[PDB]
Image (tube, rainbow, N blue to C red; front, side):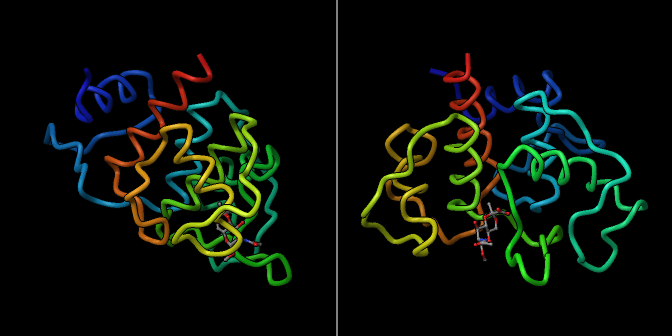
Length: 165
Ligand SMILES: CO[C@@H]1O[C@@H]2CO[C@](C)(C(=O)O)O[C@H]2[C@H](O)[C@@H]1NC(C)=O
C-alpha cells in the first residue's frame, strides 16, 4: 500500500513529475498549471515534443515559452484542446482541475466517457469525470471543478501508469 509521497518519489525518478529546489517537499497540497500538466502527460505517456508549431493564441504562447512543445504534443495527441476553439486560448497559466485531468486520462487510456452520468462536474465533463471515478483515478468525493492538487494528480498519474502497464 504505497503512499502518495512514495508514488511521487516513483514518478519523479521516472521523470514524470518534478520536485522543488533545496527541499524534499513534493508540495502535495499545492496545485498545477495546465502547462505543467501537459508536460506531465507527455512524460507519463512517452509523447514526442513538438517544436516550432503554435496552435494557440494566448499572450506569450510563442517560442520563448518552455511549455509549447508539450502543449502542442498533447494537442496533437488529442488529450487536450484548450478552453475555447474560436479564440484558441489554451490557458497555460491557469490551473488544471480535477475534471480537466479526468478528461485527459480517460482519453489517454481509451476508456469510454459515461453517457448521461450524474455528478457535480460541469456538463461537458460529467462523462469524463464519472469514467475517471469508476477507474479509480479520483475519488467520487473529489470536487471535479476544483483545481486538482498535486497529490490528486500523483495518484491519478500513478493509477493511469499502472493501467497502461
Ligand atoms: C472551458 O472549456 C473547456 O476547457 C477545458 C480545458 O481543459 C481540457 C482538458 C483541454 O482540452 O484543455 O478540456 C477542456 C474542455 O474540453 C472544454 N473546452 C472546450 C473547447 O469545450
